[PDB]
């Protein structure tokens, strides 16, 4: 994986603990040119500070809230004018209301359910449509999911249904964009201590059950996700699309 | 497998005699259940009043419920409860997506189209379950209808496939949540059946015929077949089964 | 929920009153089926002659078949055919692995242990199906018993897990092959049940209790619950279902 | 970079073998490679094919995986000759041609268990013996096909053997995880190899991939090799018990 002369858009860095910053450090270390998108002003500030650790000689930062079609459309169009065609997109974006990530899934509100779908699943479809315009000769799109999209995990509740939606999204996008030589895949990351992890009830209980029960008897980190992302975003994974790679110490393979 | 006499089921989503849910109704009715029907469009009520002539139900229990409205789901079930009392389960046979999005390129799906399909085809189960639970104090069974395009990308099913993926996860999270209440939640993954909603899906006839040539039983299924598995899932025969997706599709799920 | 009168089923693998297959037998018997039993060990026949006193079967049809022997399977079914005629289906409840291989380290499994488990626990279905087909000229249903350890690595299930993986693929390939003959083939994935064979699995009690705490219905299943799903799978209720794995396990398959 | 790494590749018969794709990728990335073969003809092919790789020494070992002794003694000797290894690529399977067509229900006991023995059990014993040369961990990769997860017409007994293999990878993953040995599978799409000739309807499947798979094309041996390099390297730390489909997306569609 030399990724020199490649360009990747990484969506969803908030701080140094973000999964997407793991991805960024690995891709940066392999020589990629990187372009970052953020929602909150504070995330841009963190990005300007985190770019000091990377070898990127230019900050390419774009504010994109994926709840707005205009921002996604205009964001990518402007990325295209600033750096040209890209080779792929790492999508590391999700949200649900804290009200809905605990207690009873059956009490989820319509508004909470559709908010989680909108940000955590639909965003991939529209990002893919707009990113395709910058990948005339192909490339690779990777989204971040969690095992709670494949099995009902206590407390993950509405986000689980959104990740089920996301994972089907990857498959329908794979099928649709295949002929354009655009691969679409997911990484199913094991639990990692991030800012968004604080929203999920029982998160610490899960970290520790991974250590005791997963095959490798340890938890994974953001850089491990990043290394599999580099695989999925590079020519190493030619032939792989519509796939869900579990970066979770083997926890998916056990019961 | 003796008998759904003294049982009461709510069947949601009959539009006409070709509806999957009318297969369910004919099987449950024939097994002695009391049945309660919910519909969105006035035309669906008219069809129901005519179809009830074929069933043995001595009383039409018809309730208008558009699952896009919380109020209608809340008030519909509350009124069902006042009219027939506690129920034993719910058959959910409801989905929708815009035709624009069921043939396009999936990557061109609109936000509004995507969320409409989630709202009607997935979220409706969650709120129906929450309101139906109140009429199942001693437990019961909820069954939703899905299709193989929620587990694999099937050409043309597009936005409805992502909605069925969402629905299938919905069944599992509901199973987990309502299990302690002795409410089982399951899905039937029906093979393609000629219905009014089938007309919305591009390439539907091509799929019917590939089932005949390739599925293990070399034939397609019908609405009554779905109904017989629904009776299993809604009865004590399936005690112990929850969070499950039963494929009623001539074995097509098992091949490649 | 009608009737298995005028139907005939072969139930393979009753050893005692706690056998999963005796759950199946009590449900099918209660529904009016004629039943035919096969056993390996002389003690299993003795248990069967005593257990038949509880059933309504007016005639003991008992046949010794060790599924490691082609001759015994071929001659057993041929003789069943001469004694009761055509059958409607087969419940297969047979497995074995050496206790040496059901604990500690899967990587230390012996070739002989591995192939023994495949032979008895998987291949037996294929040859039983081939011989049973001859007694189902107009179609029928075959059901095998599996466990979640065939789909995921469960500690201590080790070699039997690979055998159940093999068995589950077996059901699918058999479904595809025998589908055109209108013979459906399916599996029940039973949750853990206190049986004589359960004693061979390390950590069995630990698993029973984790089901109670974590599975959706917060309780374990029993043999009769397996039997009720078997009646579904062996009857016309499940027309349209083949190549399927129904989990009778309090929903434990659906969680993580 | 796989310099200073050593891998054992099991199951090259000729230049079209999946395992030779693996070899060309690992060789190109600087790995030291060790090869195992069954038939004398495969050794001859290997001595000729090694001329195309950059390996400065042929390390060839005869191992028929039906024999415990040959597996035990093969690996023990590999250890004495090159030292500790970093992983194993297993590309071995067999079933009788009689059983890879017509009716699966007519499969013989001997055919069924032969396919289990060579195509599934071989991984367990290879893993047990390879573990002894991976004191500080490593990676084991086996080759499977979609017919282990769904019933594919004509794949018949080999399908049940791949189902067994795939569960084998998961039980091995669980068991050897604590030893920092990862175990995974690659599910390769159809590739024109010597063993492909034994499967009825193989050409029909190649062409349906081109028309229906997402990428509208078939994969090749080098593509399998590139994902093997991922799985055998530190890039895939955190991944075990997994089945990666290198099949143009065909697994994701119905
Ligand atoms: N940590 C884990 O246990 C784990 C495990 C499996 C999967 N995942 C997935 O990994 C991804 C990244 O999450 P993380 O755990 O790394 O948390 P994180 O650092 O909090 O990153 C989450 C990102 O989502 C972005 N986001 C939320 N709504 C957005 C919107 N409307 N528009 C644009 N961006 C939006 C946030 O940006 P702002 O801060 O600027 O709002 C933030 O950068 C998520 O998809 C998550 O579901 C995480
Ligand atoms: N036939 C098939 O090929 C097939 C295969 C697998 C699964 N399914 C599933 O089977 C279920 C029923 O479809 P079908 O094939 O039976 O078609 P159908 O006869 O057209 O019934 C669909 C029902 O959806 C109802 N509906 C849609 N939106 C609604 C809303 N917002 N509120 C209340 N009801 C609403 C319709 O009621 P109104 O007419 O009153 O609007 C109609 O009764 C669906 O979930 C579908 O996805 C169908
Ligand atoms: N109990 C559980 O937790 C559990 C859970 C999931 C699945 N299962 C499955 O349920 C099935 C029945 O097991 P069980 O728990 O009911 O135990 P069981 O009561 O011990 O019955 C197992 C049967 O296997 C038979 N058997 C073994 N080798 C045989 C052979 N070569 N030929 C003919 N019969 C042979 C035994 O007959 P003889 O005694 O006469 O030798 C015995 O009747 C098995 O497939 C098992 O894998 C059990
Ligand atoms: N080609 C495909 O479409 C495809 C797709 C998915 C999976 N696969 C898998 O890929 C792997 C390699 O197959 P291939 O297609 O590359 O065919 P191949 O080049 O003919 O390789 C198969 C190898 O298996 C070896 N073998 C068989 N029995 C053995 C034994 N008892 N001991 C030691 N070696 C033994 C053969 O050695 P000899 O030459 O000396 O007999 C041969 O080198 C297999 O696991 C196969 O199932 C292939
Ligand atoms: C019970 C499961 C514990 C392991 C869950 C692992 C996990 C951790 C974090 C994940 O990412 C998010 C992102 C946003 C999110 O919603 C949030 C986060 C913070 C505040 C807020 O209001 N909502 C919840 C989880 C994620 O998808 C999955
Ligand atoms: C890829 C073709 C084979 C699969 C089609 C089988 C099938 C047929 C019908 C199904 O149900 C619906 C229900 C509503 C729906 O959306 C519609 C229907 C009519 C008009 C309209 O505007 N939208 C699409 C499918 C369904 O979920 C699945
Ligand atoms: C750690 C798993 C806990 C639940 C296992 C439940 C279970 C219980 C019994 C099962 O059936 C058998 C049948 C034979 C068998 O091998 C035996 C049994 C007794 C003695 C012996 O020498 N071998 C092991 C398990 C089975 O497949 C699964
Ligand atoms: C109908 C599906 C066709 C695509 C199957 C792809 C495939 C191709 C080759 C595969 O590898 C083998 C290896 C040995 C084998 O058994 C053989 C090979 C040659 C001669 C013989 O007697 N048996 C059959 C297939 C394999 O596992 C899978």
Image (cartoon, coloured by chain):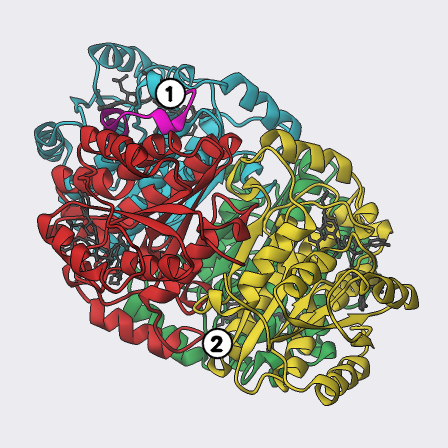
Chain colours: A cyan, B red, C yellow, D green
User: Which is more toward the observer, C77 or B138?
Assistant: B138
User: Which is more toward the observer, D168 or C172?
Assistant: C172
D20 vs C22, left or right, is: left
Q: Position of residue C42 (x, y in %)?
A: 92, 68
Q: Give the quarter the ligand 3 occupies.
A: bottom right
Outermost residue on the bottom side: it is: C82
D200 vs A12, left or right, is: right
Quadrant location of the N terminus of chain B in the rendered image: bottom right
The local secondary structure at tag 2 comes to: loop
To which chain does the residue with label 1 belong? Answer: A
Q: Position of residue D156 (x, y in %)?
A: 56, 75
Q: Quadrant of residue B32?
A: bottom left
Q: Position of residue D103 (x, y in %)?
A: 56, 83
Asked if the beta carbon under badge 1 is closer than 8 A to the nearest atom of ligand 1, the reply is yes
Q: Position of residue D100 (x, y in %)?
A: 57, 80
Asked if B254 appears above or below B40 in the picture, the reply is below
Asked if D139 appears above or below D118 in the picture, the reply is above
Asked if the beta carbon under badge 2 is closer than 8 A to the nearest atom of ligand 8, the reply is yes
Task: Name the residue carrying label 2.
Answer: D153
Q: Which residues are magenta?
A: A102-115
Name the front one of labels 1 and 2.
2
Task: Name the residue carrying label 1.
Answer: A18
Considering the whole magenta stretch, tell me its main secondary structure: helix
- Residue pictured at 39% horizontal, 78% vertical: B218
Q: CA distance from mark 1 to mark 2?
A: 46 Å
The crowding category of the residue bearing disc 1, from other C-alpha atoms within 10 Å (few below 14, some 14 to 19, many at least 20), is some
User: Which is more toward the observer, D75 or A210?
Assistant: A210
The local secondary structure at tag 1 comes to: loop
């Amino acid at each position: 994986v030399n990724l020199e002369n490649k360009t990747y858009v990484i969506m969803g860095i908030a701080n140094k603990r973000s999964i997407a910053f793991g991805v960024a450090k690995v891709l940066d270390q392999l020589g990629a040119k990187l372009v970052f998108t953020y929602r909150k002003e504070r995330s841009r500030k963190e990005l300007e500070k985190l770019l000091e650790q990377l070898n990127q000689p230019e900050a390419h930062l774009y504010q994109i809230d994926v709840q707005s079609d205009e921002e996604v459309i205009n964001g990518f169009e402007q990325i295209g004018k600033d750096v040209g065609n890209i080779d792929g997109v790492y999508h590391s974006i999700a949200f649900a209301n804290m009200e809905d990530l605990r207690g009873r899934f059956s009490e989820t509100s319509r508004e909470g359910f559709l908010l989680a779908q909108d940000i955590s699943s639909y965003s991939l479809t529209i990002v893919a449509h707009e990113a395709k315009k910058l990948m005339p000769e192909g490339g690779s799109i990777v989204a971040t999911t969690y095992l709670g999209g494949e099995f009902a995990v206590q407390n993950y509740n509405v986000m689980g249904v959104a990740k089920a939606s996301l994972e089907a999204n990857v498959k329908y996008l794979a099928l649709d964009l295949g002929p354009d030589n655009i691969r679409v895949n997911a990484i199913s990351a094991g639990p990692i201590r991030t800012l968004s992890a604080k929203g999920v009830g029982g998160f610490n209980t899960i970290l520790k059950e991974i250590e005791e029960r997963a095959p490798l008897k340890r938890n994974v980190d953001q850089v491990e996700v990043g290394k599999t992302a580099a695989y999925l975003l590079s020519d190493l994974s030619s032939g792989v699309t519509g796939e869900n790679i579990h970066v979770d110490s083997g926890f998916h393979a056990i019961k």
